[PDB]
Image (cartoon, rainbow over the protein chains, first blue to last red):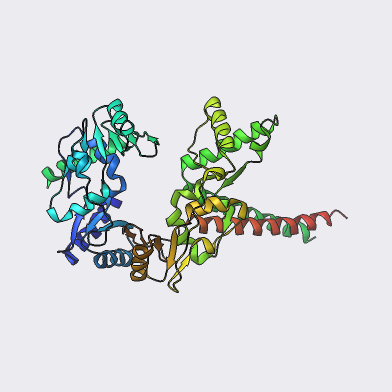
Length: 182
Length: 236
């Protein structure tokens, strides 16, 4: 059971550096509705399992403690060390969509920087045609995702891949099942 | 009168070596993955059926294989070269988009399975990267022995990551120069500040299993040649 020892080392680093290991990104955020569960899981990606810690010092400390325990390597986001750009406010004033970061809510309001880095100025649209329309029709193109998980990058690379996205979306409700069990 | 028993024991040793090589090859194959391996077998079948008829002349000598089989480095780097490249170890290096497109036409025409990702040399922009002048970070690309004709593709995969002494140094360097940084034992720090690290084993380092397979192949070839010359001059 890899998840068991993963959560074991996770709780150990949670109790070692407690004012500075906020948690993973899944246990720290959830979307506004249930519809967007697919699209959010396509935009966050590996960042869903990224551990959110306060600064780079705690990052190296947790990494070396995982190495001492010979565990699975994990990904850390240091808030103070993270390179972000402020969320483009103009894109809230949009005809057919709003930003994916506005589609999710945090849990401690300090962690906003991490959700600026995992989302940026991504946008989410109801159907595929609307996503294509606001992504390519304006004079500035934007990274847009549809509700069914298809990703419209700025370069034009259409990304489809819902084979493993069903389980990644099922983790979102399985966390509620885990909360009701505990 | 002592010859047949020594012959039998030498064949027992040869069979033990072949079983060892099958074990190590299956270890590499398990560390490779089912989709990548079936993709490699499928590219092999497409180019075999391609060269049976000799069509598309620059295409057949235009596929140069995977990234993993086009370089070799010192074993101390075997971890850190892997984790910053990842499954980019199994990208297919080809000259242009002509051969990629033709291979994929035959691919979905003959309906043969497997994942394949193509690196066409002709469409990788050579941004002349300027590497920092510190004593604290060696360029990773500098420690890779590869044919210079492929020099575009490796610059796409390794052309931004640096090897630093330890983690404090790499966190300063990566933020300072907008470059990826990674220590000798696998811990990374991105150019955006993303920390990634832990304990990387030597069991599933695919380059180390590759070198076990290659050394077993050289050993098996030496034993085969020696026993075959013994049998060639045992006919007299």
